[PDB]
Amino acid sequence: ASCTSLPSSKLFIGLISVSNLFMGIYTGILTFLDAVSWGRFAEFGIWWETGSGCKVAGFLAVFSSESAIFLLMLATVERSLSAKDIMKNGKSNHLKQFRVAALLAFLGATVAGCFPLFHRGEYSASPLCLPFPTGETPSLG
Image (cartoon, rainbow, N blue to C red; front, side, top):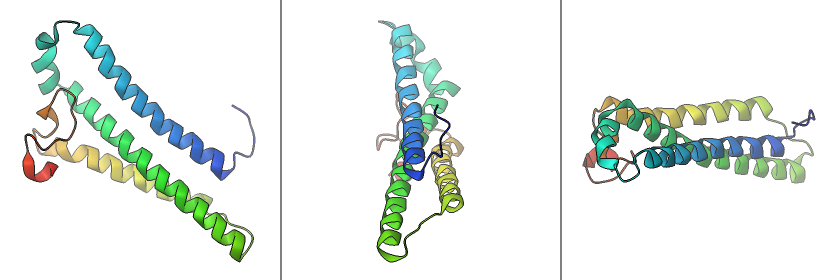
């Protein structure tokens, strides 16, 4: 909200917070669905599981988790590069490079999330729509 220079640390905190947005959104959708099915989950069970909603929620959760982890490694690598320049040169700036790396990490996360979609049955293993070694064994493992 403050129109400042937004240094690299603040931007990294912000983007990790956006990953937090998707985590919280996924969890809140879960609750919302559970509250809708208060005492009547079985009625919505199959419809949700085979429906597009389960795929959407599972992909969103997987993407949010993987993106959080990847943003974390990007932030740690950037901080280490800043420290290395501090003890080596005196100035570090890979703003465009790190933005490109963040976008590539988002691409990898989305690819991982969409991979179960093409195999027709990986995501609907559980109502939570979470990769488990219960149904499709090889790909999920």
